[PDB]
Each structure stands twice: as C-alpha cells, then as structure tokens.
Image: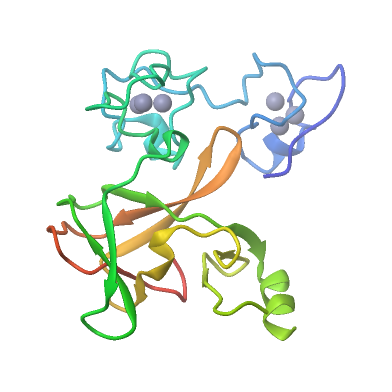
Amino acid sequence: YQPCDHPRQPCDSSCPCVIAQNFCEKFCQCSSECQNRFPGCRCKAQCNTKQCPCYLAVRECDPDLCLTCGAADHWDSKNVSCKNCSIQRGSKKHLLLAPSDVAGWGIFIKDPVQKNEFISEYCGEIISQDEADRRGKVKYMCSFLFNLNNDFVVDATRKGNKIRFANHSVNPNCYAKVMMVNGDHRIGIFAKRAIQTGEELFFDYRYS
Ligand SMILES: [Zn+2]
Ligand SMILES: [Zn+2]
Ligand SMILES: [Zn+2]
Ligand SMILES: [Zn+2]
Ligand SMILES: [Zn+2]
Ligand SMILES: [Zn+2]
C-alpha cells in the first residue's frame, strides 16, 4: 500500500489513507497511536475465523499489537495458540513433490486440512502485470508465475518454494490470499474445501 507522510499533521480528512478508506500501515509516517492504524485483536487463541478482526481484514496477527492471542509468543512452535502467524513464523503444512496424477510434476499434501485452512506461503516476488509482460518478452530454465488479480502477478522463478509446483485447474481445491504480514504483502495458500492426506493440490493460475 501507499504510506502517508504529512509531518506534524494528524491522519484526518486530508490524509490519503483516510481519503482512500484504508488503514495506515507499518511504513506510514504518522504516530504509532494514529487512530487510522489497524487495532489488532484480543482473541483468546486460534485467530482463524471471521470472529478474529485480523483474519477478517486478511491480515496475519502482529506480535506488537495482538498481545493476548499468542501472536507475541514467537519462541513457541508446537500446537501454537495463534493460528494466524504461520507466514511470519515460516510454518507450513508438510508437502510432497511427486509426479502428478494428472501430468508433469505435482504437489501432494501430507496433512489433512479443513476448508479455508492455511497450507503454505507461496514465496516469490509480487510484480505488476506490466513487469510480468516485460519478463515474458525477453529467461530461466523454467518459469513459475500466476496471476494474483488484474494488476498483480507472483513470480516464483527466482524466489519460489515447493508449492510453486502445484498444478493449475479451473476447479481448484486451493486458493491464494494476498495478506498483510508485519507491513508487507505476502501470499498465503489456503484450502478451498476440506482436503485429506495424499490429495494433489491445484489452484487457478488465471486469478486467486
Ligand atoms: Zn496519514
Ligand atoms: Zn497512512
Ligand atoms: Zn496514520
Ligand atoms: Zn485474533
Ligand atoms: Zn490479531
Ligand atoms: Zn492471533
């Protein structure tokens, strides 16, 4: 997002964040106490349903703001209380790269997953469709990209992780969410429906 910077002035009717109806983010130059900043949550635990303000706003919990859910207990890795810090923590479901049951190379999940559960971060560079076109004109052995939306693309060619091998389908069982993660947009992969162990993962490359 576009950070605001209006020294010695609050984030009022003249602040571009307030005008564009967006929260001020980590890199905005307003006070830490800016009323237009995201308040975080005060959940008991989990943070993986619409009852969590962070989850509802497509944001991971912030260790400096989400002080009660377990987001600040960053040293813990087992049966974690906040289920909305996985991208930050580098946690993912166990995945297997193997020949696809359809064709080429595929991804198989090794843990059962519920509808809308987080699977893995999809690593890569978020680039504009203009930079994606520029790259596609001029290359590597094999490139890995998908469309996030009408303006942005994720290129996993230079900075990807295993999940980049998950095949395309117009009837996918996975989807991507562009999420706010400690001031940065990062891509999360979630189950579209409940998936059982051993199932091949697919997502729609046209849009997610
Ligand atoms: Zn502002
Ligand atoms: Zn701002
Ligand atoms: Zn502000
Ligand atoms: Zn929460
Ligand atoms: Zn939170
Ligand atoms: Zn949380």
Quadrant position of residue 143: bottom right
Quadrant position of residue 14: top right
Q: Locate residue 86, reporting x and y percent.
A: 38, 37
Asked if 147 appears above or below 137 in the picture, the reply is above
Q: In the image, is 124 to the left or to the right of 198?
A: right
Q: How many labels does the image show?
A: 0
- Can residue 169 be seen? no
Q: Locate residue 78, reporting x and y percent.
A: 25, 27
Asked if 148 appears above or below 169 in the picture, the reply is above
Q: Locate residue 119, reporting x and y percent.
A: 31, 51
Quadrant position of residue 70: top left
Report the residue at 31% width, 20% height from top. 43
Tell which residue pokes out farthest to the right in this image.
Answer: 7
Q: In the image, is 93 to the left or to the right of 53?
A: left
- Give the position of the C terminus as an image quadrant: bottom left
Asked if 67 appears above or below 117 in the picture, the reply is above
Q: Locate residue 147, reporting x and y percent.
A: 52, 70
Report the residue at 42% width, 39% height from top. 90
Q: In the image, is 133 to the left or to the right of 96?
A: right
